[PDB]
Image (cartoon, rainbow, N blue to C red; front, top):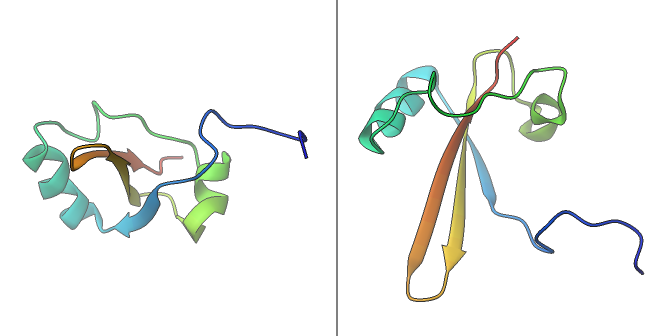
Length: 77
């Protein structure tokens, strides 16, 4: 134990969105991917969920009082 950390012990649900699906969602959320944060395909972002250059990921955060926080990340080169 006490090897490594990452802010939160557990992890959220990462889903892969199509540039189209992620497009509506992002804007549906009141934002665009250009605004949101984008992790390079060289970064673990791609290694994770086998994302490819041009794929947005859907991450949901569960909190007390039915509080769900969603954040989209676009895989960019």
